[PDB]
Image (cartoon, rainbow, N blue to C red; front, side, top):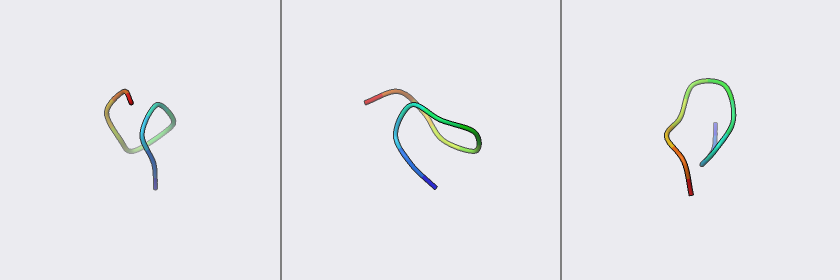
Length: 11
């Protein structure tokens, strides 16, 4: 997904 959201680590 991301950074900083659901199935991921912070930005």
